[PDB]
Image (cartoon, rainbow over the protein chains, first blue to last red):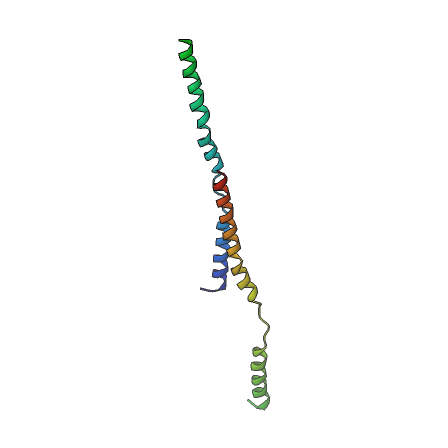
Length: 52
Length: 52
């Protein structure tokens, strides 16, 4: 190999350092949203029992 | 050939000994700068995971 190859290797690791991977904060927010579901269903259940 | 040719041969060797070529220390420095990119991206990743 020659100089151009080594410079391309450096450029490629520079590229990978700035890769645009998926926004996983969306996935973690979706995980966090489960509190609302569980607690609202608990509201529903408690309201039904109180009415009964 | 004659004396002038042989002296020109010696002179051409002298010229090649003092040739001005590209400054490759800059290429070495550009190679060394890739650590900063890698480690800063590691900072970014670790901060994101800690926040999550």
